[PDB]
Amino acid sequence: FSHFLYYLVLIVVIVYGLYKLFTGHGSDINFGKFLLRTSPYMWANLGIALCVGLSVVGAAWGIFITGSSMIGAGVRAPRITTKNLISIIFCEVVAIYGLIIAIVFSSKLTVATAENMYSKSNLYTGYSLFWAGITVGASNLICGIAVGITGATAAISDAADSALFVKILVIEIFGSILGLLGLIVGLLMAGKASEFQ
Amino acid sequence: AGLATVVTFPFMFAIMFGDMGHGFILFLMALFLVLNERKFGAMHRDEIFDMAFTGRYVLLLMGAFSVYTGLLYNDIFSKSMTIFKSGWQWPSTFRKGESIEAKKTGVYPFGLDFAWHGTDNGLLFSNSYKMKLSILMGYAHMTYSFMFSYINYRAKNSKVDIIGNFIPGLVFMQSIFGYLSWAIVYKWSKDWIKDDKPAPGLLNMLINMFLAPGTIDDQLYSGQAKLQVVLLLAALVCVPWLLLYKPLTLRRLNKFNFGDVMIHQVIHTIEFCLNCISHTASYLRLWALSLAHAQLSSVLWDMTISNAFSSKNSGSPLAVMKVVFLFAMWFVLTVCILVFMEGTSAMLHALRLHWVEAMSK
Amino acid sequence: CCTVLSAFGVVILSVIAHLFNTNHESFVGSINDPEDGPAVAHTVYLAALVYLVFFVFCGFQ
Amino acid sequence: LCPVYAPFFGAIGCASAIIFTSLGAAYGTAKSGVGICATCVLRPDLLFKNIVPVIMAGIIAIYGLVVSVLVCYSLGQKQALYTGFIQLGAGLSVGLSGLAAGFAIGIVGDAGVRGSSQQPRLFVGMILILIFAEVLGLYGLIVALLLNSRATQ
Amino acid sequence: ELCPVYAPFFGAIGCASAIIFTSLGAAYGTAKSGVGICATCVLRPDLLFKNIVPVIMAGIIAIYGLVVSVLVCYSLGQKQALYTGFIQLGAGLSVGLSGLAAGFAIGIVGDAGVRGSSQQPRLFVGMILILIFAEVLGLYGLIVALLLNSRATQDVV
Amino acid sequence: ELCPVYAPFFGAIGCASAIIFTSLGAAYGTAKSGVGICATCVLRPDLLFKNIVPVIMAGIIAIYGLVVSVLVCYSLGQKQALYTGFIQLGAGLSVGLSGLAAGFAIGIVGDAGVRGSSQQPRLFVGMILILIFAEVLGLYGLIVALLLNSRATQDVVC
Amino acid sequence: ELCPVYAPFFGAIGCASAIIFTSLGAAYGTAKSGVGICATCVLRPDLLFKNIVPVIMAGIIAIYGLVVSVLVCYSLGQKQALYTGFIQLGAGLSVGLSGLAAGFAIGIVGDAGVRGSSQQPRLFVGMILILIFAEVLGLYGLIVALLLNSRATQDVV
Amino acid sequence: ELCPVYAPFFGAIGCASAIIFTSLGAAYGTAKSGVGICATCVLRPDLLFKNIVPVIMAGIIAIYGLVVSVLVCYSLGQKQALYTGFIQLGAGLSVGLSGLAAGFAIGIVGDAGVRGSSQQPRLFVGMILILIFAEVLGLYGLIVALLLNSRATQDVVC
Amino acid sequence: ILSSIWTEGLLMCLIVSALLLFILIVALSWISNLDITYGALEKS
Amino acid sequence: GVYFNIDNGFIEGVVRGYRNGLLSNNQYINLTQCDTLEDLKLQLSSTDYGNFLSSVSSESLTTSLIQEYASSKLYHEFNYIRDQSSGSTRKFMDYITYGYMIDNVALMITGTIHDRDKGEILQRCHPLGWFDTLPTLSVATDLESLYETVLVDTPLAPYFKNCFDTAEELDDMNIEIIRNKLYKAYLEDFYNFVTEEIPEPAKECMQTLLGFEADRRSINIALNSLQSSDIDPDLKSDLLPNIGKLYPLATFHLAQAQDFEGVRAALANVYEYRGFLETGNLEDHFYQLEMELCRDAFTQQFAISTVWAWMKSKEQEVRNITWIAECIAQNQRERINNYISVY
Amino acid sequence: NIYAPLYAPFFGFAGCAAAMVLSCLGAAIGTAKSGIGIAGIGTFKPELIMKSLIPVVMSGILAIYGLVVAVLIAGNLSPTEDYTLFNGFMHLSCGLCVGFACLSSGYAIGMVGDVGVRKYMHQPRLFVGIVLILIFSEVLGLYGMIVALILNTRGS
């Protein structure tokens, strides 16, 4: 039924675009004026909220992936249940990344005067906070899921042999590069963005 | 079929692999195996190097023809050669940064002209030239390998096979795509600007020769509208003739399964009339892979050593280690891609042009 | 395999340095090309000498 | 500057701050309560120490209730789009965070209360895993309570 | 402008959804945890009247929806503000989509609990304790909707 | 108005479609029949250059797409009629979405034919017979697209 | 106004759709019947040219599209009425989505009949008799589009 | 009016698509064939370098996409015609969604070919020939896009 | 102006209420996939 | 591996823990050095079997009681893993036990033709293949009155689709036909279940583990039909499963295989089963290939095929321990190292 | 200025986000799917693990490929300088042609370098072929990064 709706929305978009284009009014579907006239606080607050939301839905994702297999693998070998908690920690740090980026973004969130409200800088710092919240929340989502998967494999290879956890912790390190790189990119994107003035 | 292969397979390779720089590298690494064929013959060869040393004379010809054709093009590691006198002169007094044209003085003596190198519309001219080159060389290869069928049926002393397969095949192939290959040469022969006549489009000439006979929008030669009807009727009369001559005259010479001959001749007619169209469009890979090789060798030069050329810091250690590192990065990428993992594809495409487009006539 | 790359580094970069020195229009003749010919030839010819050092050193191996 | 559609975002933020948080808390209660009911048919003396995942899922819903109450005391007819979208962000933050934290507490909790009946050393393990999944609701509550303080300034 | 014509639409959707989604939640809680009663009272029917507590705690969610639907219904008007319609939409969704979650949790916990309480009679107190935490979700949604609906028509113009 | 600015869009996505939807049917006819050649010629490798006719007849419809894409390409212009763009879109769809069908049919028939022609050698002439009917479905689309493209710039004005 | 600029769009979509969906139906009817033939005569190859009837009857309903996609193609002009484009779209859809159904029916009946006609020799007459009813579907779609296309430019202005 | 400000959008997404869908097809062709290489060279180690030809054959598809995307990139302009953006969008789709098809075909042919060529040594030539017929689809897409891209900026104006 | 029907405020209420409804549909599809381990509740 | 640990997180990690109790080659060599069944019990007590024969005490300890209790703890571990399963996993666990239900049906209705007592033909039945109406197969003789009375409410009811009851009640010749045909329909249904609802990493490595069961059953049916069967190939082809690697070309030649060479030349064309019928014990070849296919099913992580690969490996472990304890109790040690160890 | 409208940095920060998110998605698929195959052979021959960490490193390089272009797009974005819509479309395209390039290259490395590592415990001669197929599947993202760098220098 979802494929029927995906086809129906696509058919309605094609029929509406071709009807609007054939009648000489095709510039009325104006995405640029939509970007110019929507409020920058929508993009800013939506970016902050999706940053701290999608970091947590990746952190909590990885926490259950390498938590349920840690508890399952700890039934026969209970000497992993404290040492291997660093795999919970590596997928938990992607939430503090999104938190400390969301607070730094919300510091740039003041009341702009209505005479200069849809200005160049106010609209720039809405766009920048939106996409720099998206590129941090999605990167921490994907990093939390990857660290959870490579910690769920580590929690079972630890219970197999003790000398394997040191060898497969390296894969968790290379997986946890990603959230820190998103942390860097989201600070470079909203680095030149000013407050709302 | 391996006695016409000995020239045509390296040459159909070289049409796709056209460069004097990569061609000289391939010729040199082939001549290394030819001059050392006594030390390598009494040696255990693994499968890849056994493949490379069994064909140490296919690669020598594949390099020797690639040097010739990359001297026909101006393509020496995707650069031009100002060997001869140009047929195009540029204006002397012009403003900086504006778009200018060149005036034709003469024609370039051997090969393509070097005033098409840093040119905006040079790639359109190379598309037209290499497309018509592929059409004419595929036509030549097909009409050369189609005469071997006549020599086979003459050596078998079977006039029934001649009149049933060769002649209705010959005046079907030559009446359509022989006419196309003649029309390309005749458009190249006429000037169309000094004559103040419109240059005809040859795609929608062959489209309109089958759809709307007798209607010629842009006239290409005198008597076109009545000769194309004769060629169309000569091509359409050989669809029943190649399908109905041989079974109906094998049946007449029994006065043997007529169902095993009639169905076979219907399949032969459908296959041959399909393949006359399907192979002259399949020889355009000689233009496809040549365009791919030329453009990849251009955009590798432009990314690697066009960055290393700067008149600042002349003699500095950083500015010379820049050139060293970028030449190393360029050379390993040319050898790894543009020779080994591009000429192998050109080799295999010149191979399938023999296995299908030539060894089915 | 460094001696092969070094021999090509002698030959190709020496020809490129000579074509920058003589102001050949396939290397200098465009606006995006470098302005001074021998200034680029002086830093390509030194790279040709560096690859000649690599060719002589790896030629005794 | 303060349009007529501006308290839509604040009212829907106050809605979503309890809706998504109660969905996460309901998943964390139901999935980890199945593990309690499945575990305590063969070893019933672990019934009141396995009750910790549904308590933590309830704490998540309390964190969402706090944001919903604190958003609905700043709603007005003539508030700006600034207040409206900042209440929307304060709703979305604690909504996605409580939803994620409740899903994580639910999936960790039943596995933990099943491993705790086979190995007694896994009770401290499941508690130390569930404490990391609990504070993710706090990590959204921080952004929600910071965006609440910038409502009318 | 402050009181448009399309403003009772959101108020009527808020009056509808408060009873619709809590009836969905209570229906799942009655359904899933009544299948367990009908499956486990064919062997021990003496505890038929104590397994009914998931069904009752599921049906409390529909009363939570009914209260908010009546209180939104008696604040609708033709010339109400768009603010009032937005608040009534929010108060309808805050009870409906939270009591839907509470009813999902009550149905799952009740079906898992009345099946395990016939094999272990000590699991009944734990089932009641988990169902209280499942029912306070809908109670929290009721609190949020009452605090919205008190704010609905307060200083409206 | 009669030759608008957005008029080459339909001609460009008709030049593009006639090779896209043609080559992704030719790819199905190559892949689905090539896994039937590579799984059959492990025991009968003498039939290798005889069972490869489904792959050849799947490659022929891509040439059918190539011809129509070239003929639609060389009739594109900056200021062309919107009728010409509609006709070129129709020709591109007529080649592409019917050569896709011909490639599906060649792919489904070809592996069933080459897996059966090694148990019974008298099924090869039946495989060719079914496969000609499966392959003429793209030739019909080529005929429709060439009759469209001959009508594209015939009596266009403005 | 009666002959707009966007009027040949519907005629070109009809001329394409006349052959596109009949090629899909003919492809299905050829594909399943070819699998049925190639799986039914590895043991009895004497029925090879006898069982070719579903492939032929699936190939006829693509000629049904090739007729109307030429008769619509030779009525496409630059300045044509929108009524003509609407009828040509209706004719293309009437042949296409009916020959697609006819091809589905021929493709199912074809392999279901050639896998069973290797056992019973007189199921061949029944297979032909059902495939005639499956091929008159495409014949009905052809009749509908030939009656439409004889009206697309009858009394247009 | 004829060279609008939003005109390089179509050329930009055409330059993007010729990398996106072409690298997606090349990645499928390398991944699915490398599964078969790593699955058959367990007990056949000497055929490890004869089996790379599907992976190289799929990498030439990404080289085809790379060439056309770079050659589109060096014709993007700020004051670009909308016809030029339409042509570059068509040339990007014509390489991308045909190289995706050729990559699907090489990925499905090549693993079956390296699984059957470890069992039958005479199936290698048939595998190479079917892979040539599968790579020529992406070659056709490159031919269409190079003939199409050469027509962008021929008679553009305003 | 952007439009008269699809104004600047309606069209960004229908994006917020589409994101929230997407999160709602995802979360309800998570809770709908929640099944009980019945074998650990029976006697057998 | 992104949606696996929702319902299967605890289930895998315990089964992965159960995998680590598989005896290695050194733990088998330490069992082949034993002199007494008591020494073998004390050697197994240091493994993860520890104190499973504690209620025996050295007097009633036979080599069949070891096979009883070592398999009984396998069955209780399987029941513990199955009780924590829900949804598609629990259905996958049920589909494993259906193949043991078929063997218990075919073992229960042969104990009534021979008029052996119902209390002793049920202790030989398999504990995982238990359904509630299994003792009530001792009520009728013919197939129709055992289907329409008992086997309709069983989950083996869709598998009686080709068992043609010609009103001949039962000999020992057609109960094996009913057994092979039920197992044929079961292999079809469980392959379609694996292809349909099981996710993709646990799909490709479970279709191979199940097609191997189909190929082994095809070769065993086509090879046991030489000695104790005189049947037509059109009736023999209804016994061979059609899901495997061996079906479309080789089970045809196994259907008309009238001689041993008709089997051997049919299995010479398939690549991984050639050489099984040449040298050595064929049953050891199938068990070795089973363990080599179960070994590389543990190497894919987020897969529910690890349950199948665990229980078949643990059954081979119980078979190896039973073979060793049979060797060290009957004092024959010429083939004590005939165990199969890939772990 | 009609060529530099004020909504143009939307498509530049979209280029940043498409260059980072999809490239780290490809890097994460490539490291997680391959770490599954590396840890799967953890018990069977544990000595081949530290040699088999190459499809994890080559997956992590795909995040550096997106990092470089994300830094180079974010360095061309300032609220005080003029920023054309051509530049914004160009940054959208150069992030979009490196994100799906690194995504496809990460899918290819993840599908190759776990099957290869998982079959490598049987045949120790697979490693050269595994590294070779990983190089052919890792230059897929290098192609997209080359296009992104040329496109960034063209559009500014």
Image (cartoon, coloured by chain):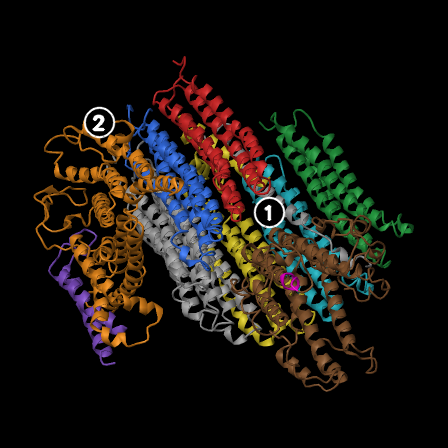
Chain colours: A yellow, B orange, C purple, D cyan, E green, F blue, G red, J brown
Q: Provide residue D47's location: percent of width, then percent of height.
A: 80, 62
For mark 1, what is the residue?
D92
Q: CA distance from mark 1 to mark 2?
A: 68 Å
The answer for which chain carries disc 1 is: D
Q: State if disc 2 and disc 1 touch (CB < 8 Å).
A: no
Q: Secondary structure at mark 1?
A: helix
E9 relative position to B246: left or right: right
Residue occupying image coordinates x 83% and y 44%: E56
Q: Provide residue E30's location: percent of width, then percent of height.
A: 79, 43
Q: Provide residue J319's location: percent of width, then percent of height.
A: 69, 73
The foreground one among D99 and J57 is: J57
Q: Nearer the viewer, mark 1 or mark 2?
A: 2
Residue B9 visible (yes or no): yes
For the magenta stretch, what is the residue range? Answer: J221-226
F70 relative position to D21: left or right: left
K62 relative position to E112: left or right: left
Q: Does G147 lie within the magenta span?
A: no
Labelled disc at residue B217: 2
Q: Amino acid at mark 1?
A: Leu
Residue D79 visible (yes or no): no
- Furthest toward the right, the residue is E46
**In the image, residue B205 above or below residue J209:** above
Q: Does J224 lie within the magenta span?
A: yes
The answer for which chain carries disc 2 is: B
Q: Secondary structure at mark 2?
A: loop
